[PDB]
Length: 99
RNA sequence: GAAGAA
Image (cartoon, chains in turn red, blue):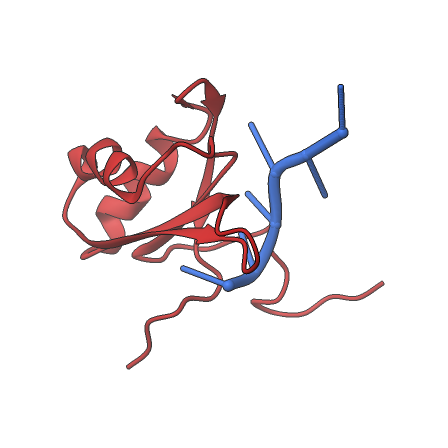
């Protein structure tokens, strides 16, 4: 079947950017930042939204200022509970920032 | 009556 480096998403690798999945529709970027900034410094946080209704799609991303604090948070928050939903967490394979 | 790369 189909397969490619950094296109596959069930086999991530370390990155300052983390993805967060399973979220409740009432979660804000501020709740994610208060829950993840206890593991280290965070420059930004962004929830992913529907284009026609502006509701959350159930996933988001968290941008640390260091890969080793992202390696901490990725192991800390994977399988935790937030607003009555379990969340899962992994390193970003791709991201909106670029340099 | 998916909880996954924007």
